Amino acid sequence: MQPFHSPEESVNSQFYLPPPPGNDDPAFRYDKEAYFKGYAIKGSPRWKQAAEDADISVENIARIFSPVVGAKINPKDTPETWNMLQNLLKMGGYYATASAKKYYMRTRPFVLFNHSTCRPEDENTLRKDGSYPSGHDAYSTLLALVLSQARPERAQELARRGWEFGQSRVICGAHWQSDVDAGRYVGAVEFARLQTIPAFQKSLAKVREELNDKNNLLS
Amino acid sequence: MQPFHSPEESVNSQFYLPPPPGNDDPAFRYDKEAYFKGYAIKGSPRWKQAAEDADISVENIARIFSPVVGAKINPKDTPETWNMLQNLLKMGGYYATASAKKYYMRTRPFVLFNHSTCRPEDENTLRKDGSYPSGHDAYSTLLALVLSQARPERAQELARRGWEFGQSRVICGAHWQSDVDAGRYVGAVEFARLQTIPAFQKSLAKVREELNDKNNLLS
């Protein structure tokens, strides 16, 4: 599997995004209220939901989205969809966010307040990485849009799932609300950039075939 | 020109959007703070810029986006681009937001605080219409993405301009910050849905020609 494009062929997120809020901004006051709101329900089911949502491995991504698109997603039955899930992680999670991330190097909520997140295993990786904008949310957003393109029949369920991911990220404590909001817009910009890349069109054509194949449909 | 699709073929926004922030919500406290901050600069340059962004007439939209996409947009030199701008106002401004707007009928900020907006000539219409999600922002986002598909080398400028429109809407006082965020996402969801419609693809192919035509280029 070969990347749809290079880091330099992402749209420069540092150019189009506004800077992140300072501790004096009303948007930061919202950021921290939303953080403590999420932290207040530690241990609960919704919190456990958020730990499940928070894993960005392709296996987890597949298990979450499969019931949503209404088709099997696994390396055997849907090999191209499986590659597409991973290709879009690199494109949307890393390439699309990278220059704004590195520019601002925004400090994560859990580090600032000395708490643990809903997913302690990932914490040390996340410390080294600028919060803003959220690459996780750029990724889950791009994913929802591509899958909506391949399976328009399930667009409304895909868009709902795409929104809910953001609520999970805020609850898990590794992103601020404002990271999530900027991440969503980044995911749409990358989605638009992918439409003009022939390799992406070629792979989407096969994904559409896999997910609409009667043999792959659920239930 | 004829509509890319029917009202039924937009994704049901009532299904995938959350309810708007209510009386006690932190997001709502943020909505008010961002409203106050915007009215407090009544009369400034920024307020005059916002007044100009607020006009969604095709003539004004074309004037704004022209320098940004780097080509002339007018009925004579770019007839399909002209139709495309009108089609997307219907698709994105109206069809894509309709079920959520009707369902919630959210009161606008200027009404809740007994004020004027930055564009009083439009206040009569806007009064009739629910705030959430923002159709003006769904539209201006859809437009920015679609033009990015046509001239991908101007994608960073178009992405920036698309963000700035949102900031103008919050300042003008006809929409809450949370309407604007929800409208951006709606515009992306409609953008994905349009990718699946042949009439849109045919029309985009002509737009791409018009806008990269040497006779129409511009700086």
Image (tube, coloured by chain):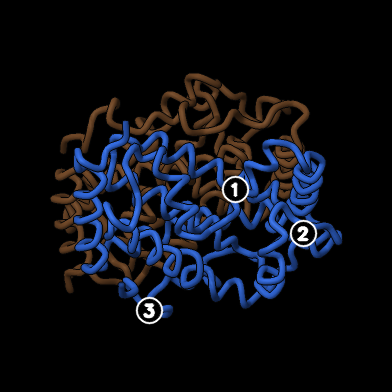
Chain colours: A blue, B brown
In the depicted structure, whether residue B110 falls above or below residue B61:
above
Name the chain letter of the residue that bears numbered label 1: A
The residue positioned 39% from the left and 43% from the top of the image is A66
What residue lies at 58% left-to-right and 72% top-to-bottom?
A100
Q: Identify the disc placed on residue A6.
A: 3
Q: Position of residue B25 (x, y in %)?
A: 74, 33
Tell me which label, 3 or 1, sits earlier in the chain.
Answer: 3
> Alpha-carbon neighbours of circle 3 within 10 Å: few (<14), some, or many (≥20)?
few
Residues at discs 3 and 1 in contact (Cβ within 8 Å): no
Check the picture and name the quadrant holding the C terminus of chain A.
top left
The earlier-in-sequence mark between 2 and 3 is 3
Q: Secondary structure at mark 3?
A: loop
Query: Which quadrant holds residue A34?
Result: top right
Q: Amino acid at mark 3?
A: Ser
**Chain of the residue displaying label 3:** A
From the image, state whether disc 1 or disc 2 is nearer to you. Answer: 1
Indicate left or right for A168 with B34 as reference: left
Residue highlighted by disc 1: A52
Which one is in front, A45 or B46? A45
Query: Which mark lies nearer to you, 3 or 1?
Result: 1
Judged from the image, the secondary structure of the residue bearing numbered disc 1 is helix
Task: Please name the residue that numbered disc 2 is placed on.
Answer: A109
Relative horizontal placement of residue A41, taking residue B48 as reference (left or right): right
Counting from the top left corner in percent of width and height, residue B196 is at 22, 45
Image quarter (top left, top right, bottom left or bottom right) of the N terminus of chain A? bottom left
Q: Position of residue A138 (x, y in %)?
A: 50, 58
